[PDB]
Length: 178
Length: 161
Image 1 (cartoon, each protein chain N blue to C red):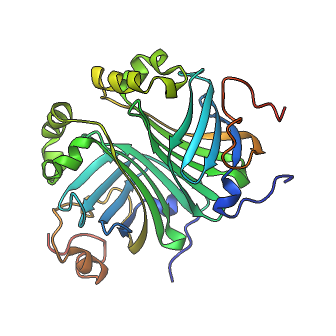
Image 2 (image 1 turned 90 degrees about the horizontal axis):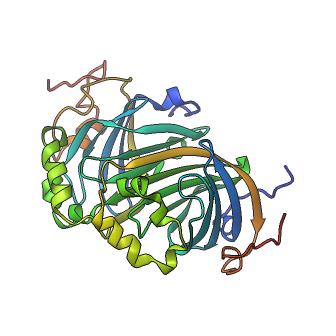
């Protein structure tokens, strides 16, 4: 039933939920050509969420897309989306301090950039926690680009279900609860 | 299309590459085995640097496309995506600030100076990182086989042009 992803435009504006093979559940939105929003539902930093993260986004080859970014925490990320196979592979390179004090980062990051930057200078950076994992995509929605509703509140337990069940977004892909 | 079609992980492993990033940086790189890479930098910011037995995660994303992730003694993180059937790659290198500030420190046979890399990454600034996400053209491929210790050393392999 799903459209074939063939171009950059096909990919930009798409809203994903996926589960890594380590059990971590992420939600991620290609908000525009150089911007990503995301929200973390399961894993070491579940509850953490992020908007307006600058990123490099490329189509590597027809229907396969690579996203690269570095965070206020000092974390590096390389994601490879294969939407036509409902698969992804992500490598996250966490500073030592995120592994040892993950709770610091479990917040709306945008409200606490200074805390992220003070923590990354106060605590240990090495050795890195490197997490390279395949994931299965469990949801894709066409949000359009620059849709500020997609990722605009903290995650709650039922949210992935509500989104997948069509209970979260209205006909214009805006929040029913807002 | 003289080149064999890459379809499995075994097809990729043992392959010796040379590639040039769009910015002009030139790398020579070898998939020595399922978890280990050797490489030598020929041009750019850190030309002259080389590395053996860098532990890495190596996976096939999908038929004929291969992703390699590793982290370095310098603190640098790397994610490479090889598309040998298109003679193309895309690399993202995330350098700590200090490598951009003092690239000459890293220009050596890294294996003999692990201590220096680790001490440097604590001594100098990490942020802001220099992130280099770029496509590269693959200009050479050779089948060296796995665990071939002659591919990357001080001397040239030159079982090739």
